[PDB]
Structures are given as C-alpha cells and as structure tokens.
Amino acid sequence: RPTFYRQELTIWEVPERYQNLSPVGSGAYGSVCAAFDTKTGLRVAVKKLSRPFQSIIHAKRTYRELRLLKHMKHENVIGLLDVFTPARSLEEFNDVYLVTHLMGADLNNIVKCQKLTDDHVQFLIYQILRGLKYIHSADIIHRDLKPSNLAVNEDCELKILDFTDDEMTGYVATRWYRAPEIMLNWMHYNQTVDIWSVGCIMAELLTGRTLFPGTDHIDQLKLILRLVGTPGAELLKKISSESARNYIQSLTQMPKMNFANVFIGANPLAVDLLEKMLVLDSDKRITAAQALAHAYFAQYHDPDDEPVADPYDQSFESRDLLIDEWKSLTYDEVISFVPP
C-alpha cells in the first residue's frame, strides 16, 4: 500500500507519488486535479469520483467505468494509469480515484487554434478508426463520439476519451454527431453508430463546419435526409417503430446528393470515404477495420500495427445486483489493478 497524504482541494487522499495537485475539473461525475506523477514523470489527471455507490445505478456506473477503463490498452484510446482508494478494507471503502494522462486539448480546441490540412485530417481520422477497430473488436461501442472526446496532442497524436434527453434537445453538439437510428430510436443499435459519428467529424474537419447542425431532432433528421436521401424500403422494414416508419413515410422522397458537389475541392478519396461512412442503413456502412484499408490512408495504413483487443466480458450489464454487490465488484477491481 503506498503512503497517502490528505489535502483539502474536497479532501483528497492520494499516494505521495502524486504531487502538486491542482484542481482543474469537477461536476457531478467527480472532481479532477492535474498532478505530477513523480514516479512515472507523467503529467496526470486524478479524478475523485462523486458519490460512486450512491444508488444501484451509480454503483453500476462506477463499476462500468472502471471495467471499461481497465480494459483499454491502445495508443489511441485513453487507458487507466492507476486507480486507488485510501481504504484499507471493503468495510472502509468509499472513495475511488482514477488516474489518467493529463490531456492537452481536444479536437475543438485544436481547430479553434488552427486550420487543419488534408494531411492532418488524414492522420487524425486514421487514428480514430485505428482506435475504434480496437474498441469494436472488444465489442465496445462508444455511442458518443464527438470532437470534445478526442484529445489531440502537440504532435497531432490522438486518443479517444470519455466513452439526458434535455441535454440532447435543441441546437446542441451533444446530438449533432449521433446516428439517426439512435437519435430517433429507429431500431436497436450496434457499433456502426460510431462510424456515422466519424463521418460527421471528418466532414467537419474538412469543411470547418458542423455537418448537421440540427436545431432539434427533426430538423437534424431533415438535414441528414437531404444529404443522404430518404429511406428506401429495405431500411424502412428495419425500423421497428410504426410511428417512426409512418413519420419517415410522410417526408417527400429525396435522392442521395452528389458528395463531390457538397464537399467541393476535397480530396476525392476523402469524398469517397465520407460516402462509405455516411450511409443511412447502418448495415451497409464501412467498418473501422475496412475503412483503415481505404486508399485515403495509404500513407498511414499498417495492417501489422493496427491491433485488436482482448475480449471484454460485459455480462454484468445484464445483471441485477444490490448497491453493495456492485460496490464490492468495484473494490475487487480496484485492488487487482496491475499498473501499466
């Protein structure tokens, strides 16, 4: 067990390897301090979770995040550098702290400061798909990819990060990258959801503009359908909601637009990739693995440096358990943490 010192920044009790903690973040998830890991020389983010086992749901959520973060071992995905609790036994256990690389800036911040170049776009999207091949191989779905969840360092190296209905109403970035099928609950979703988000992110990097700045769900749908065309019959069959099907049916049929006239002057290989990603029917979208083989990434594509993940068992998602059982599974995961 390391030695822990306590200081009030909230009271943080952290191992003394973590020095010079400086408060930088907070919010109902947890407070975040920036710190210097003397032992790895890394600059780190230390998150003290807010109320982790306050409710079956919160306990299960705590558990899920820890389980996810401990799984991820890939250049382009955030991983867990460390997790700890000052508690010396399950009975004492209450606080969870998660330690990750202090991140430089997210993709939005990059963009605010810079005009990107097709080479930058090439490289940045490559990395996302590389990360996602890994993520998807473990059958994990990020379901919330957005420029704010992508951390880009000074060398254009990127990590996928992070992983309520009012918060998705209106003119909001929380919804603009969402695949239609989940934005309107057309059908059960799967990983193809993320490739849609990548299409939206890529286009925006190529144009400097939100691809679908919907003012609300229905406006956004209209924007999507104008670009990709309204649903044909095959996909209609797959939307299980009769009302949704009905509503789509009320909209005047429109054909796919010409993407070369929408993304004027973009590299045709980018244009071609966008069309493969932005397909309304999820079943027909390109997968991250396949996209990585797309000519647009010839300068970066290495099939022997694009690894897949170890299995992620998420059977717990189907499990109903009491707070204290979730809590105990979390304590277990805390204490088995093997450092990187």
Image (cartoon, rainbow, N blue to C red):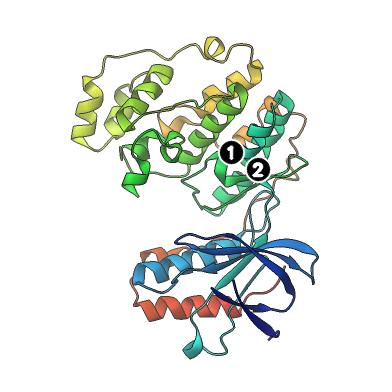
At x 46% / y 46%, what residue is drawn? 143
Image quarter (top left, top right, bottom left or bottom right) of the N terminus:
bottom right
Report whether 160 appears left or right of 299. left
Q: Mark 2 = which residue? A: 130
CA distance for labels 1 and 2: 7 Å
For this orientation, the residue located farthest to the front is: 8
Relative horizontal placement of residue 48, taking residue 212 as reference (left or right): right
**Coordinates of residue 309 in the picture (x, y in percent):** 62, 55
- Residue 319 in view in this figure: no
Tell me where residue 253 appears, x and y as whole percent: 30, 14
Residue 73 vertical placement versus 18 (above, below): above
Q: Residues within 10 Å of mark 1 (few under 14, many from 20)?
A: many
Residue 154: in sight, yes or no?
A: yes
Mark 1 vs 2: CB contact within 8 A: yes
Residue at point 77% right, 30% down?
299
Q: Which mark is residue 288?
A: 1
Disc sitting over residue 127 in the figure: none
| Amino acid type at mark 2 | Arg
